[PDB]
Length: 264
Length: 264
Ligand SMILES: C[C@H]1CCC[C@H](O)CCC/C=C/c2cc(O)cc(O)c2C(=O)O1
Ligand SMILES: C[C@H]1CCC[C@H](O)CCC/C=C/c2cc(O)cc(O)c2C(=O)O1
Image (tube, rainbow over all chains, first blue to last red; front, top):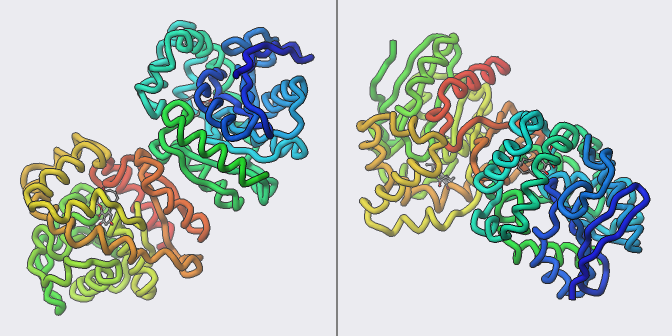
């Protein structure tokens, strides 16, 4: 039975969060769009292996929109990490396994490095480390132009699974619609240079498991593969592209549980 | 002005070859389809920077089809490397820069390792190290079935540039048509295990420059990126996929000249 509720933290954020299961804590941090419905099936599937799974909409996104501006403008990994630590503090999650893609991947690595006592192990997927001008240039467009362009880009280029993307439903896509402008203005310029992945050695020997999408063009996260290999960090593939939890929920869920079981 | 001619070597092969330019030798070794007209523009463009450029159809392929069966069945990097050393012997090329993609990539690294006195530097692109059952399954079909399927697969999936691929013309596509079966039967089972990349320390400090296609799915050559990084070998991207010399001739040519100038 899934808890669907709100909890507030003293940095001014009111988080929408979901929680199911009993057992060691596993936390699913969204990608930049900040929408935790993307995890819905995997929440249940990972919980059914004996885990308490918690996820949430990210600050300023979807149903966690009640948040002050610093929390969704000039966003950095280090900022997100501290927001995530504060919602963990509120929910009394002391020791967590954490997953994150994209800005969520940067967040989890910054969590692992900054709060090692708190993080049992971290799985990061497709960690952005490069400025991408086609994304960054949308910031200066009109809100509805941004939503049209980014919605299309997710649907056609990066979903990894067009049908599964569209099957999330109208409600989700209506929340994403409003998030695309806030993401565009707040994330693409400032997340990449915040990447906590330039000190290779600090990554060495850490409980970190890195993935890239199998179908993602080799150029997008070529640099993740080099960096992981130079740091001896485990690196592999998940099917699909930027949203394996949408396109391949069953393999995603099994990967989270199997990687979590390694570190208990 | 380009030389277009044949030369026979004592392993029973009659090679079709082309050559243009004066200067240090640069040799362009085809991919598995063995068809050197794919290089035509780049031959002129690299020569025009002060190089003597040589290429050729590969044994059993295209206009180098007069060759004994061992030269195009159970093909191996080590076999292809000896075949190319013989055509270089015949043509009196003592020192060469070499390029190769796919089976050509395996050939060039085997050349570099096996004949270090002969190879100034090698550029390998998308070196196949894994058995691929969808490719190997085509071996047991009808010849004309194999040509249909592979001609379509190159056109639509892996050219990196559909217009540029088709613009090579009817003559080249008529030669490829006959090569697809010979390749299917001779290459995909035996070329991957022959990959000369399993000894990391032999690669280290060698004049080797490795590339993968930018648009190629991450999974196809993930392993090349890990291997290069573990051996300190330079590794980067070219635009397109499996045939940058077809899809992006100008940037391919400039990459060959620049990388050759580094080592000269
Ligand atoms: C939401 C998702 C966008 C996917 C399409 C993007 O085109 C995928 C490109 C990879 C980088 C995305 C990205 C970059 C960035 O600077 C900050 C981010 O939060 C992301 C990110 O979260 O990626
Ligand atoms: C002809 C070229 C493109 C084949 C499409 C392939 O589907 C592209 C995937 C990479 C594999 C290429 C390949 C594998 C191999 O074991 C031996 C080979 O000679 C090649 C190779 O030459 O591939």
